């Protein structure tokens, strides 16, 4: 049977497009799907490898490897072999000669980069692609009438950078069209991360962007090279709408919704946002002899929201040693009122694990991830990729310090989850099983 189901997935069989009352257009099933089933795949309509990963990944197929070959002309684009080089040429052409001309003045933002490739795919290929079997880039929603003279000013920067760096092999539409398009990208664009959650690049998957949002989703989006796959994490029955999450589901219901309104212009009405069952445990209060009063909680919460924004902006400025102090002390304050499973505590613990890893303090980074994992399993849903990568980190750290048994446990915990989300076939599942076997 295995042959037929790959074909069905590739063609989006057993699914359809419809109008979701109160959510524009959307996607629903016309057959049952069990937990771990592949629904559909969607090859990338446009993509770009992030600048800081050149030399580690091939630009065309995203394979991670050593001994890639360098572009003879510009020396700033790498490939598996000559086949991958030829296939990337229609796109790489947009930057090759310019990178040589501008030297080190060449710094277009990743948003500009990806939009240039969209424009170039439209001259070459005006008609409907295999990425667009149910929704087309042309049809993408913009939220143009909801924007303001902060946002609209930000786009006009990108429009200028596009004209400045790309005029040579693109001809541009009128300003009105470019503003709409840059808004469409924001509403429909995807990021790609690796198994440790480092940024790799950006891309457009049109069929994938038909699906609407829920904080208790029933599918999950994973990557295989530049290809997107979609697998179920709850049982789905005929006539039922198919939902992803668009955001990190760790945080409480207020925090989630500020983000959704800001980036996507809507308010979620799902069961977790209605009942708010998990909010109380995400903001778990210390149980002291004289237990903390109500105003003393509103204090530590607003302090915590701000020490996250301070740290966000401090990543571009400061020393590693100074950032690790900012985490230590911010935890040290919060621990009087908040328990160790409070998500605002867990936030700073994660950032501190990041700082310890760049410093190669592997024992120091290990007891952060030890305190993280059990709370992460409680707050997140079943089959969460966030939970899976943290196990993965623990597995690797344990084995770096020669403690085989606890490392093998943590690696199998990660594989258990990945089987459901990435499928049993996945290249990652092999790569981890070779860490086991040595
Ligand atoms: O950009 C979006 N999502 C990106 C967040 N990325 C999460 C992700 C996936 N795989 N991995 C890598 C990964 C691989 C192996 C493990 Cl064990 C762990 C991790 C990260 C996907 C997005 C865009 N929208 C548009 C529709 C509004 N919604 N979400
Ligand atoms: O929900 C969170 N992140 C989600 C937003 N991320 C995906 C994303 C990004 N951009 N775009 C739109 C976009 C993508 C590519 C280009 Cl070229 C253009 C546009 C999607 C994932 C989140 C992050 N945190 C941090 C505090 C820990 N908390 N929640
Ligand atoms: C990537 S799109 C999804 C496709 C969209 N329905 C369309 O066809 O234009 C994101 C947009 O869909 C809408 N949307 C997604 N999930 C929603 C929800 N749970 N409630 C209301 N609107 C939602 C929002 O308007 C959001 O900006
Ligand atoms: Zn390649
Ligand atoms: Zn080149
Ligand atoms: Zn919700």
Image (cartoon, rainbow, N blue to C red):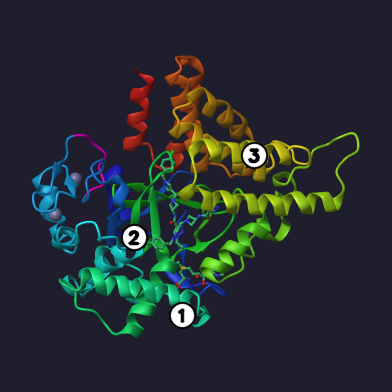
The answer to if 252 sits in the magenta stretch is no
C-alpha gap between disc 2 and disc 1: 21 Å
Quadrant where the N terminus lies?
top left
Task: Report which quarter residue 88 is drawn in.
Answer: bottom left
Residue visible at 17% across and 63% down? 98
Q: In the visual, does 301 lie left or right of 249?
A: right
Quadrant including the C terminus: top left
Instruction: Check whether the beta carbons of the residues at disc 2 and disc 1 lie within 8 A of each other.
Output: no
User: In terms of sequence position, does the residue under pointer 1 or pointer 3 come before the other?
Assistant: 1
Q: Which residue is mark 2?
A: 110
- Find disc 1 in the rendering and name its residue: 144
- Residue 391 versus residue 181 in the image, above or below: above
Can residue 91 be seen in this snapshot? yes
Q: Under 8 Å from ligand 2: the CB of mark 3?
A: no
User: Please, what is the dominant secondary structure of the magenta stretch?
Assistant: loop
CB of residue at label 2: within 8 Å of ligand 2?
A: yes
Labelled pair 1, 3 in contact (Cβ < 8 Å): no
- Visible in this render: residue 140? no
Where 183 sits versus 437, above or below?
below
Numbered disc in front, either 2 or 3: 2
Q: Is residue 208 left or right of residue 46?
A: right
């Amino acid at each position: 049977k295995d042959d037929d189901d790959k074909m069905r997935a590739e063609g989006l069989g057993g699914l359809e497009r419809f109008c979701s009352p109160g959510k524009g257009r959307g996607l629903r099933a016309l057959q049952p799907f069990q937990v771990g089933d592949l629904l559909f795949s969607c090859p990338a309509y446009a993509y770009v490898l992030t600048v800081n990963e050149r030399g580690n990944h091939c630009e065309y197929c995203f394979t991670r490897k050593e001994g890639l070959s360098k572009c003879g002309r510009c020396k700033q684009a790498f490939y598996c072999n000559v086949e991958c080089q030829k296939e990337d040429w229609p796109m790489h052409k947009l930057e090759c000669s310019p990178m040589v001309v501008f030297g080190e003045n060449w710094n277009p933002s990743e948003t500009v980069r990806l939009t240039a490739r969209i424009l170039a795919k439209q001259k070459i290929h005006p008609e409907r692609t295999p990425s667009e079997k149910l929704l087309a880039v042309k049809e993408f929603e913009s939220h143009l009438d909801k924007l303001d003279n902060e946002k609209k000013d930000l786009i006009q920067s990108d429009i200028a950078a596009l004209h400045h760096f790309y005029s040579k092999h693109l001809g541009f539409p009128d300003n009105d069209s470019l503003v709409v398009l840059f808004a469409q990208v924001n509403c429909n664009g995807f990021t790609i991360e690796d198994e440790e959650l480092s940024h790799l690049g950006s891309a457009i998957f049109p069929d994938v962007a038909l699906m609407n949002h829920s904080c208790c989703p029933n599918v999950i989006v994973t990557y295989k090279g530049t290809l997107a796959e979609v697998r179920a994490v709850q049982e789905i029955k005929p006539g039922e709408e198919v939902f992803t999450s668009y955001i990190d589901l760790l945080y409480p219901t207020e925090d989630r919704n500020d983000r959704l309104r800001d980036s996507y212009f809507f308010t979620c009405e799902c069961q977790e946002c209605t009942t708010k069952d998990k909010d109380k445990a995400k903001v778990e209060i210390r149980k002291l002899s004289d237990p903390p009063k109500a105003e003393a909680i509103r204090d530590m919460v607003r302090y915590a929201r701000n020490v996250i924004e301070e740290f966000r902006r401090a990543k571009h400025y400061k020393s590693p040693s100074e950032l690790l102090e900012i985490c230590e002390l911010s935890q040290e304050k919060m621990s009087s009122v908040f328990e160790d499973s409070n998500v605002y505590m867990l936030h700073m613990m994660y950032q501190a694990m990041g700082v310890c890893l760049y410093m190669q303090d592997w024992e120091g980074a290990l007891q952060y991830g030890q305190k993280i994992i059990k709370p992460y399993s409680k707050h997140y849903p079943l089959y969460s990729l966030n939970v899976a990568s943290m196990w993965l980190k623990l597995g690797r750290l344990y084995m770096g310090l020669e403690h085989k048994a606890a490392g093998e446990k943590a690696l199998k915990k990660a594989i258990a989850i990945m089987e459901v989300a990435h499928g049993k076939d996945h290249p990652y599942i092999s790569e981890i099983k070779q860490e086991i076997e040595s």
